[PDB]
Image (cartoon, coloured by chain):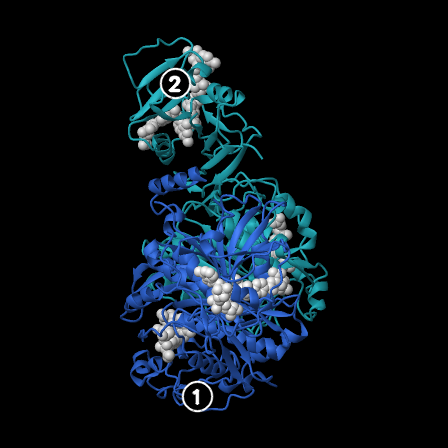
Chain colours: A blue, B cyan
Amino acid sequence: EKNVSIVVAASVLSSGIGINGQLPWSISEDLKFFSKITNNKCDSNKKNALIMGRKTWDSIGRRPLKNRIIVVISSSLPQDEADPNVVVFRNLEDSIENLMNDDSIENIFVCGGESIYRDALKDNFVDRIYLTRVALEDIEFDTYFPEIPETFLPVYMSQTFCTKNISYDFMIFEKQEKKLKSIDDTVDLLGEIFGIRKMGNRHKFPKEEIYNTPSIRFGREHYEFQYLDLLSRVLENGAYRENRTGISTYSIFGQMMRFDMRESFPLLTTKKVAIRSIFEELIWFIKGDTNGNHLIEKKVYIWSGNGSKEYLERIGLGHREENDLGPIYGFQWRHYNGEYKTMHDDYTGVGVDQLAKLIETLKNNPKDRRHILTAWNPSALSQMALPPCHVLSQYYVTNDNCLSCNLYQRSCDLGLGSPFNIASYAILTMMLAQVCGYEPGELAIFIGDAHIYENHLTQLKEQLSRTPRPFPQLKFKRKVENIEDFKWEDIELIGYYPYPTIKMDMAV
Amino acid sequence: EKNVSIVVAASVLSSGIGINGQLPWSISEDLKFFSKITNNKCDSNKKNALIMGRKTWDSIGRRPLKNRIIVVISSSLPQDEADPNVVVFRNLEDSIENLMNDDSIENIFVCGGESIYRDALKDNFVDRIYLTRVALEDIEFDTYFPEIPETFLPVYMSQTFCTKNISYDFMIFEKQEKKLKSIDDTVDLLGEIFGIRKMGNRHKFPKEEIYNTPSIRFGREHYEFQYLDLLSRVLENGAYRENRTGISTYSIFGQMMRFDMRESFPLLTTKKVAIRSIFEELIWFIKGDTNGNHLIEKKVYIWSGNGSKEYLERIGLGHREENDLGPIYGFQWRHYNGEYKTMHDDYTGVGVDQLAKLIETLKNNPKDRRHILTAWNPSALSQMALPPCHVLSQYYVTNDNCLSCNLYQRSCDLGLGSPFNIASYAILTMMLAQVCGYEPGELAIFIGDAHIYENHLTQLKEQLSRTPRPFPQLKFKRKVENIEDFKWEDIELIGYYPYPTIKMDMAV
Ligand SMILES: NC(=O)C1=CN([C@@H]2O[C@H](COP(=O)(O)OP(=O)(O)OC[C@H]3O[C@@H](n4cnc5c(N)ncnc54)[C@H](OP(=O)(O)O)[C@@H]3O)[C@@H](O)[C@H]2O)C=CC1
Ligand SMILES: NC(=O)C1=CN([C@@H]2O[C@H](COP(=O)(O)OP(=O)(O)OC[C@H]3O[C@@H](n4cnc5c(N)ncnc54)[C@H](OP(=O)(O)O)[C@@H]3O)[C@@H](O)[C@H]2O)C=CC1
Ligand SMILES: CN(Cc1cnc2nc(N)nc(N)c2n1)c1ccc(C(=O)N[C@@H](CCC(=O)O)C(=O)O)cc1
Ligand SMILES: CN(Cc1cnc2nc(N)nc(N)c2n1)c1ccc(C(=O)N[C@@H](CCC(=O)O)C(=O)O)cc1
Ligand SMILES: Nc1nc2[nH]cc(Cc3ccc(C(=O)N[C@H](CCC(=O)O)C(=O)O)cc3)c2c(=O)[nH]1
Ligand SMILES: Nc1nc2[nH]cc(Cc3ccc(C(=O)N[C@H](CCC(=O)O)C(=O)O)cc3)c2c(=O)[nH]1
Ligand SMILES: O=c1[nH]c(=O)n([C@H]2C[C@H](O)[C@@H](COP(=O)(O)O)O2)cc1F
Ligand SMILES: O=c1[nH]c(=O)n([C@H]2C[C@H](O)[C@@H](COP(=O)(O)O)O2)cc1F
C-alpha cells in the first residue's frame, strides 16, 4: 500500500492535454514542476515510478528520466531487461505490482496520456491528482484529460502564474476516504461564555454552505479567494442595515483584499466582468473629466444612475446639468481644491494636479513614503453627486523596480463596485508602472463598509458556487508618452475564460 | 493512560491565587470557565475527577460539583463513602489511581491550591495547564501558583476580557513530548521554481527566532500579536531601503492590524508605553492646535525633533518659528483648507471643522457610510513640518451601538509611531463614543510603509522576547459636554502591568 498520484497539465475548460503526439504549449516552469513532484521522495535509497503509455513514451524521445524509473504500458514493446531505468508491462493492472511486492519503490505517479489517465481512474487506482490548469482554449486538441470523478475533491489551488503571456494554476485533488484538538474546544467554550463580547464570535468563520469550494481548506492560495471569501464573510457576519437607498445591505467593517499583478491580472473569473467599462471609467478619471455623457457616449452607463436629473434634484443639485456629476474622481485627481463651476468649463491650470505630482514623484524619489493620491475633499463634498468610495490610494516602489498599490475604500458594493475597483486600480497601477518605468507589483485593497445589497443575494450566492479559474493576462500593446494617451485598443486581454455573466441591479 | 490537566486562575505577575482561604477577586466568567472546562467530556457515561486539597475543599463550602467527582486530598479527613460524588485520599500519588484502575473516569483535573499544584508539578503528573491570568497585583496574597516549569510551553492565549474593570486572559500550556502533509510540499516546490514570482515568497512566514512566543502556533488570539507578528513579518521580509533621514529602514507594504476595544484597551504590554504623552498628543489634535510648545510645556517632547530650528530650515521652513509645525493633524481636523499664517493667529471659524461634522453625523445618521476624517490636504502639504502619517480615518456604528474605527497609515514607525497610533486612535474612538453615546468597538489599522528603523533592531528584538500580558482597561471618570473638554485627570488606566520600557531614538 503506497501512494499513486496523477500529474497532468490540462486546459482550463476542455481539459486538453495534447495534439499530434506532443503538447499544445511549451511552458518551461510546468516541466520543472513535473521534475520536482516526481522526484520528491523521502528515502534516499528508493526511486519513484512513472507510469506512461507507449505513445507518451515516444513523445518524450524514448529516453529515461534521471533518478526515476519509467514504467511503459505498451501492448507490443519488447520487455528488455537491458535498461534498468525503463521497464515495460502489458496492462495497467499488472503494472501496479510495485505496491505490495517492489519495496524498492516509494511512490507511484501516473502521467501517461488519456488512455492511461482514463484507465487509472476507471479502475480506482489513483489517490491524488496534480492538475496544472492552463489558460489556452482557442487551439486544437486531440487528447483530453478525463473528467475528475466525484470521489475527488480539490484541496489546493495555487496562485495564477505566467509564462509567455499564458496563465496557469496548480491544483491538488484528494480522494475522499471514510466518514491542537484541545485548543479548538477551549475557544468554543469561551465563545459560549462571552456571547458577542469575544471578538471571535463577531467574526465567525463562514459556514460550508456559503464557502466557495469548501474542500480547499489550507490551500486557498489563488487570490480570487480574497474576494470570494469576503463575500462568504459578509454572508456570515453581515448585519442587516439600512442606507441612503431603499435597498438594505448586510454590512461588516474593516476588511481587506490582496492581489498579485506580477504574474496575473486580478480580473475575477467566477463572473464575466465588463472589462471595457472598467477601463473607460479609469481613463475618464485620468483625463480630468467629470462629464457623465462622455461615458454614455461610449456606451458606458455605470454613472447614469447617479447622474439622472431626477436623482440630482433629489440630493439638492437641481441647478446642475443632466450628467454633471461634479468634482469627483478625476477632478480631485487633476484639479484638487479647484473652484468647480460646471463640467463644460476649462480647468487647465486650476487646482493641484495630484496625478502629475504622483508620476513625477514616483520616478524622481521612488523610495519616498508620500506617493498618495486622495479624493476625499471636505470642501467640495457638498458639490459632489456622490462622495468618493475609493477615497485615498498610496503607491510603493520596491527594490526590484515594481510598483505596488494600496487603496482604502470607505464603502464597497461587493456585488458591483468591488469587481470594478479591483480591476480599475490594477490597471491604474500598471499604467503608472509603464509611464514611470517600473513593473506591476502587488495590489492591496482596504475596505470600511464592505456590504452586499439584499437584491444581490441570490446572484452572489450563485457566484460562490463556481470554482475559480486562473486569472487572465493584461498586457499593453504600445508604450505611451503621457498617461492620458491610453486607449481601449491599447489593451490586450489574454486568456480570460470566465463563468457566464451575472446580472445585478445597482442601488441608485 | 488518560489526560491530567490543571486549571488555575493566578495573578499576572506574582501568580497569586488566593488570600485568607478565598479568592482575591470575584470574576463570574472565570467560574463559568471552570464549569465548562471540568465538564467537557466525550463519554456520556463517564465523569471527570477534580482533585483538590482540604483547604480548597473548605473554600467551596464542602459541597459537591454537579456531574463531577471531587477528589479531596486531606491528611485527616474521614474516608466516608456515603457521598459517592466526593472521595478522599491520603496522598496525591495514591489518588492518581484513576489512570489505570477506575475506567469510569474520563479526564482528571487538578485545581486544589498551592500544596496540590506544587506537588502535581514536582512529580510530573500534569499534562496540560489551563491558566486564567488576572490583572490584579497591588493587593495581598497568601497562596500562590508555582512557576510553570520549563517542560511546559504555551499553545494558546485568548483575547483580553473584562469583568468589573478587571482584565484577564485564558492560556493553555502543554508538556513537551519527543523531538495537509502533501499541500505544504507542493507549495515548497512551487517556491523553488518561481523565485519571487510566487507571491508567497514575498510574504515569507517569520522564522522561529523572530516569532514572539513561537510555541503559540494556532492560538494567537491575543490582539497584541497583531502588532508583534507585524514586527516579525517586517524582520523576515523587510527590504533595506533609504529614506529622507539618515537612518535606513526595513520596509514592507500593505499590512494591517486589528484590535478589540470592547473588553480591553490596545495598549501594548511588551513595553511600557508612555500613555500620558499619547493622550496629550491626541487632545492636542482635537483642540485644533499646531503649537509645538504646548506639548513641551506639558513635558511631551515627541514633536520636538520635527520642530527644531535646525530641522525646519533643513526642509525649507526657516521662516517658521521654533516649533511652529504648521497645518498638521488638528488643523485639517478643525480648519480644513484654512489659510495657515502662523501658530499664534486665531483660526476660529476658518476652514472645515471635520470633527464637528463627524460628531454631528455620528449621532444623527449612524448608518451613514461617510464618517470620514481626513488629514491629507495636498494644498497645504508644503507648509507642513511633516506630512500626516495617519492620513485618513473612517468610523462605523454597529447595530449594537458600538463605534468601530478604521485608519489608513501611509508610513508606520513600528518602533515608536505604531504603539502610539494604536492607543491614540483607540482613545479617540472612545472619546467619540462617549460624546455620541455609543460604546467602543473594534479598531483596525491599515498600513502602507510598515518599517523598522535600523537603530531599533536590538530593541525590537528584545521586545519580541517578552510573552505579552493581558491588555489594561481604560475608563473615563466623567462625561464631558464637548469633546475638547477631556483632561488627563479624567482618564483612569486600570490593570496595566507591562514589561520595562524600551528606549528607542527617533529618526529626525
Ligand atoms: N499535458 C500532459 O500532461 C500530457 C500530455 N500527453 C499527450 O497526450 C498524447 C498522448 O496520449 P495518448 O494519445 O492517449 O496515448 P498514450 O500516451 O495514452 O499511450 C497509449 C499507448 O499505450 C498503450 N496502452 C494504452 N492503454 C493500454 C492497455 N489498456 N493495454 C495495453 N496497452 C495500452 C498502447 O500502446 P501500444 O501501441 O503498444 O498498444 C497505446 O497505444 C500526446 O500528445 C502526449 O504528448 C501525454 C502525457 C502527459
Ligand atoms: N485561584 C484558584 O484557581 C484557586 C485558589 N485557591 C485558593 O488557594 C487557597 C487554598 O490553597 P492552600 O492554602 O495551598 O491549601 P490547599 O488548597 O492546597 O489544601 C491543603 C490541604 O490539603 C491537604 N494536603 C496537601 N498536601 C498533602 C499531602 N502531600 N498529603 C496529605 N494531605 C495533603 C492538607 O489537608 P489536611 O489539613 O487534612 O492535612 C492540606 O492542609 C485558598 O485561598 C483558595 O481560595 C484554591 C484553588 C484554586
Ligand atoms: C510525459 N511527459 C509529458 C508531460 C508534459 N507536461 C506535463 N505537465 C504536467 N503538469 N504533468 C504531466 N504529467 C506532464 N506530462 C513529459 C515527461 C517529462 C518531460 C521532461 O522533459 N522532464 C524533465 C524536465 C526538464 C526541466 O527541468 O525542465 C525532467 O527532468 O523530468 C517532459 C514531458
Ligand atoms: C476550587 N475552586 C476555586 C477556584 C476558583 N476559581 C478558579 N478559576 C480557575 N480558572 N481555575 C480554578 N481551578 C479555580 N478554582 C472552585 C471550584 C468551583 C467553584 C464553583 O462554584 N463552580 C461552579 C460554577 C458556577 C457558575 O457557573 O458560575 C460549577 O458549576 O462548577 C468555585 C471555586
Ligand atoms: N450604489 C452604487 N453606486 C455606484 N456608483 C458607481 C458605481 C460603480 C458601478 C456602477 C455600475 C456598475 C454596473 O452595473 N456594471 C455592469 C456590470 C455589473 C456586473 O458586475 O455584473 C456593467 O455596466 O457592465 C458597476 C459599478 C456604483 C455601484 O456599484 N453602486
Ligand atoms: N520620523 C518620525 N517622526 C515622528 N514624528 C512624530 C512621531 C511619533 C512619536 C515621536 C516620538 C516618540 C517618542 O520619542 N516617544 C517617547 C517614548 C518612545 C517609546 O518608547 O514609545 C516618549 O514620548 O516617552 C514617540 C512617537 C514620529 C515617529 O515615530 N517618527
Ligand atoms: O467604484 C465604486 N465602487 C463601489 O463599491 N461603489 C458603491 C459602494 C456603495 O454601494 C455605493 C455608494 O453608496 P454610499 O454613497 O452610501 O457609500 O457605491 C461605487 C463606486 F463608484
Ligand atoms: O503618528 C505618527 N506615526 C508614525 O508612524 N510616524 C512616523 C512614520 C515614519 O517613520 C515617520 C515619517 O517619515 P515619512 O514622512 O518619510 O513618511 O513618522 C510619525 C507619526 F507622527
Q: Residues within 10 Å of mark 1 (few under 14, many from 20)?
A: some
The picture quadrant for ligand 8 comes to bottom right
Distance from mark 2 CB to nearest ligand 2 atom below 8 Å: no
* Residue at mark 2: chain: B
Q: Secondary structure at mark 2?
A: loop
Which quadrant of the view contains residue B85?
A: top left
Residue type beneath disc 1:
Met
Q: Residues within 10 Å of mark 2 (few under 14, many from 20)?
A: few
Residue annotated with mark 1:
A343
At 34% from the left and 32% from the top, the residue drawn is B41
At 31% from the left and 70% from the top, the residue drawn is A244
Give me the C-alpha separation between circle 1 and circle 2. 88 Å
* Residue at mark 1: chain: A
Q: Is residue A192 visible?
A: yes
Residue A191 % position (x, y): 36, 43
Residue annotated with mark 2:
B101
At 51% from the left and 81% from the top, the residue drawn is A492
Name the foreground residue: B80 vs B274.
B80
Distance from mark 1 CB to nearest ligand 5 atom below 8 Å: no
Name the foreground residue: B315 vs A162.
A162
